[PDB]
Amino acid sequence: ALKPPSMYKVILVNDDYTPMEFVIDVLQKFFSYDVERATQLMLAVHYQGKAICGVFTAEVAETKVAMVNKYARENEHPLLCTLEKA
Amino acid sequence: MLNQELELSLNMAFARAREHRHEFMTVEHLLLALLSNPSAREALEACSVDLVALRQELEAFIEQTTPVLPASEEERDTQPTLSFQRVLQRAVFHVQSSGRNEVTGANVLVAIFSEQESQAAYLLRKHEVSRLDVVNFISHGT
Image (cartoon, rainbow over all chains, first blue to last red):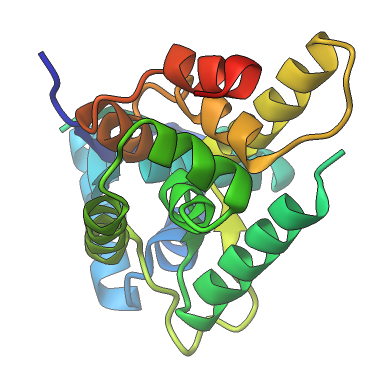
């Protein structure tokens, strides 16, 4: 009757206002990717419309999502970060 | 109004997370620190919890799932999860709701049950402990 909480995918969603450079900034600053990998993920967001940035516990995923969204808000970009059950 | 023992527990748990370079201080770091907070420990012993086992389960989970800040990263440091923040606010709310002010480790433990998607709440229920078991211990001992 008891199952562990599940893991969550943290996702970056595409939009037409947010600069590629800021998406890369976010991937490096909040997910620790190096420039190369961050750039690949930025392109994926651009083409697929969204991309998985990482998988974390529900608790950690929720916090990363809030942190990314606050940072986007602060810099006035509508960059949307979301989470989804893994 | 956190009592002295809880405050000490919270601050040392936080210092330990910072020494380990953990990006986040979780509700699991919190429950782990409460295992030796007198107030919360007494409640868990009253519920016949294998504290040695719970401790190991928490440490293993913390180690496998908590991101580690890189050496380079010297601009950001350990921060509490939203879940952790809610538990502390909830513990204060519950205590004030009864007209009191002193918040103990046991009240914090009670609040953990409300974070339904936390590994800590899951491990507590797995060790057959319910919110009401803890409230009963706080209200009536045994």
